[PDB]
Amino acid sequence: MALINENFLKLKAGYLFPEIARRVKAFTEGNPEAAQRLIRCGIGDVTEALPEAVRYAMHEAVDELGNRPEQGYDFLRNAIADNDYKARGLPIEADEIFISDGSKCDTGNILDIFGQGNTIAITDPVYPVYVDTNVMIGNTGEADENGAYAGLVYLKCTPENGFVPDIPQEKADLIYLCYPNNPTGAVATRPQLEAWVKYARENGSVLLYDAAYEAFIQDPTIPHSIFEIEGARDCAIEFRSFSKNGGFTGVRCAYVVIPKSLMGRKKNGEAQALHPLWSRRHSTKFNGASYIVQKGAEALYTDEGKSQTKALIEHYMGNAALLVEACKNAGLSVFGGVNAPYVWVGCPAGLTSWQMFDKMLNEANVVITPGSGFGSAGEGYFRISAFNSRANVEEVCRRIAALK
Amino acid sequence: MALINENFLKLKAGYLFPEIARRVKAFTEGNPEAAQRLIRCGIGDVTEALPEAVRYAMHEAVDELGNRPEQGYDFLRNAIADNDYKARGLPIEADEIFISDGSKCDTGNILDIFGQGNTIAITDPVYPVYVDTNVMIGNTGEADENGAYAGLVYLKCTPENGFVPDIPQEKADLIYLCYPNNPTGAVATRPQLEAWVKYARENGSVLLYDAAYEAFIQDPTIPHSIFEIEGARDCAIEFRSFSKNGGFTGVRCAYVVIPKSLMGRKKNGEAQALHPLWSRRHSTKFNGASYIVQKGAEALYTDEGKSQTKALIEHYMGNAALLVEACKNAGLSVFGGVNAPYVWVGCPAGLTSWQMFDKMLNEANVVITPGSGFGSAGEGYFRISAFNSRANVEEVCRRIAALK
């Protein structure tokens, strides 16, 4: 018989979000009356998954394919290089941009170009894809009581330390930073990124910088890109998303930035550029994002596209501001809701994250994400998405206020 | 410094198709006059990448996302189960269907749920994704002079043996079969598949059955699906594509069939179902195919969709028939062009595959695929795609006849 990948059996449970969808469906089946009242603030529940400019461009592209490069089309790689980097004085070229189907895929699949035995550092709590894919490829040991896997170096982010992780004494080879952080909403300051780039460069490490929620930053002092930091070109890969941007989950498109100067080592100690490794991976294991979605994403860089995106970001951060107010008024400890389209909330005394999940589902008829789903440091908290209608978030705010 | 995946350095060259695109671009730069005359029969050059029914559905879906499950939507999983399996008396359920962005991705990424040290058998020559991804994950040794990697069991398909591989004396754990074969155009008979299912079941092996060109089969005696064979449920995964079907490369959608009954082993020898392993992989490392492309693919199962698909298949197999006639008339040994939309052609006396590639580019201004690109058994042949306009294929036929 054919040997299975036993690293999959190390996984304590199923992937968080399908595990939630299961428990919601179970509730919905048993409670048809409640199901009609249900509001989804887990992943979220967007109305306009495509702005006008993007829809127009996608219709044109559909007709174009009727009439009629894995790295991505020139027009989109150039639009990204020009608008997100060159126009901000950042040293990134179009041929360092790799267009994908989403950041979930890129952050998951980046480990394909790295070997075994690397020391992996991951911010805790964070988006659980980084941990789970590290377990699957065999970069960890078993999980403990609290679902932390041996071998991984967990950088603890708490209210105590303002959700800014202490740069470790341990020397990590790969470092996952999510900024703005999902789910805490935390942002890194310029000096904090300067210190991370210093640590990475002197240890010859790689910063895996997930900037998916970049566009929601409101504080004008906060960096958007790691390549705002001198020397980032020598130690940083950046993940960006069109889909988790402006809540247009319909724009299933993202990109990875790999400087041609970025180096790993072989077993013999000699240097090896990461750019070619990823290019080979991208062109062999992926078939490229469609012309339709790439034309959609190009539309986001038009005047009308930027105008439509800015209104949606104001709408969603308006939603977040109301969730912060309602939680504060109800006596709950609240973090974020100012630089990312979600809020991080302390569970009421004596409730685990999963117990608060069940209470909100059964009593308030509101889906939230249990904090423990984002790692051990997440226990005692939950996340509420600001990705919903204004009317639904106002309703959720009333339900949180009324929670007994 | 961070350790790279050394398995990438075992790869003799870049992935075949980007390697061709490079050599064409180089020629196009140096020869602007020739570039105007160039006809692309490598990958191919389709005009209508979307039928009417698919475009209508994609336009409606774009507007739907403006107004208001990784495994794939119910509507498409049900349409596939009902039309491609149940309506042919095949025992496949909707929950055994996994919707993806393409077969290249699925056939490449299937190795993620298998361990190391399995004996891998691959038909030679074949689509080079299977070999290259096996090299990347560390399932092989180094390449030899002819680009065959140590460890892999290569099943030789030649004119001598009618492109029928000998069922090996070696006991293989994973077996890659491509039917119709890319690039030879060969098809397996019912008794040949019966023998493969017998071998697989008695050795507890897994058949990885790539049926991407299923729709182009013209011989009514030839099986379309491995699940036409009694016992396939105990030893078979099937790969199907909407995109490599009817030449609609615009429909970036495919699916994998994993029976819930299909078993691998752990290191202690106990059984483990493959279905859950793939579900966890699919929901963690992938973000699901878009609603727009899934609505597109659904449209292919309508009366108008089947009618439009059948006309395009007749158009492309008409193209293949002309390529066979022109090659035969010019004194070239030709195989296939009857059950798949490409022809497999013997190089003129004394030319390697790459030498025939250069001759067709420089003398005829025609891109073809060198046979050696599909493995060692491919040397001395080349592939011509039937995916082009009728006028372009008639032109290519004249240019082959005029080749001196």
Image (tube, coloured by chain):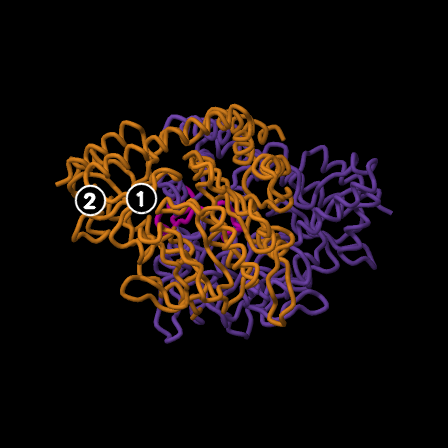
Chain colours: A orange, B purple
Disc 1: which residue: A335
Q: Is residue B63 left or right of residue A60?
A: left
Helix, strand or loop for disc 2: helix
Amino acid on which the number 1 mark rests in the picture: Phe
Mark 2 in CB contact with mark 1 (< 8 angstroms) = no
The residue that disc 2 covers is: A27
Q: Position of residue A214 (x, y in %)?
A: 46, 40
Asked if labels 2 and 1 share a chain, the reply is yes
Residue at figure coordinates x 77%, y 51% from the top left: B357
Report the residue that reaches farthest toward the left: A404
Magenta extent: B83-107
Q: Secondary structure at mark 1?
A: strand
Which residue occupies 62% across, 38% down? A86
Q: Position of residue B41 (x, y in %)?
A: 70, 43
* B310 or A290, nearer to the observer: A290
- Pointer 1 chain: A
Of badges 2 and 1, nearer the viewer stands: 1
- Residue at the far front: name it: A191
Residue A328, image quadrant: top left
The answer to whether any part of residue B298 appears in the image is no
Q: Which mark is residue A112?
A: none
Confirm whether the magenta stretch covers residue A162. Answer: no
